[PDB]
Image (cartoon, rainbow over all chains, first blue to last red; front, side, top):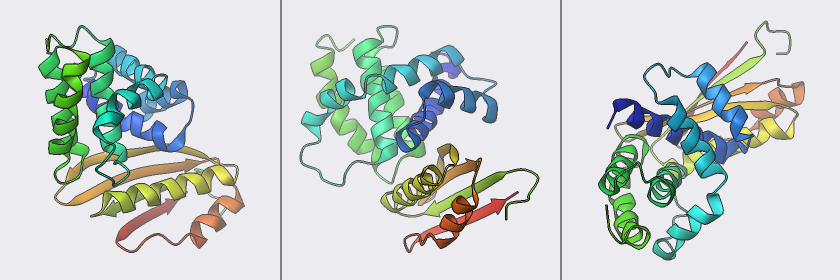
Length: 138
Length: 85
């Protein structure tokens, strides 16, 4: 896939984090990010689609996630929550994004912005959640 | 204070604990929004070592914003840099 798509995920992790903390209108959050962050190499369409995708679907995306969280208790990190919401969004709503790509990009996004062993927890949730969303695993 | 040409407060946070840094960030954001201000970001930076980085800017601050920020005591193990104007 294009590096611009990966960049869009990276920028969406940051912007969705903005929104999670600020609860500003996601349109404003999109605009502000496009005006203040270097975005020259970014799939700007997909960035928009990831943002609104997640921001208007938080309840649905958290619900797909919850059954695999109910026990390991440290609230859940804001970066991890954004990474997981992106991954689940792609798995539920984006057929143009392949199964292994959604999970692999999530794992790398967690490596970059996440805590110490964030990638391993993100991995744990996803390959429990992903087969339930994509029985074909494609 | 107040009369500074660019009415913008830039904040950079560092910490080893992401629970501490997300909480501190939440509190700064809340302080801005309580006091009639607006927030740009916050955004997380790529982690380097054991260190989490957060950037948050406050625009349109009131005097109450500035006073409340300066009265704000963040958790031990969270480092800050603040620039005004």
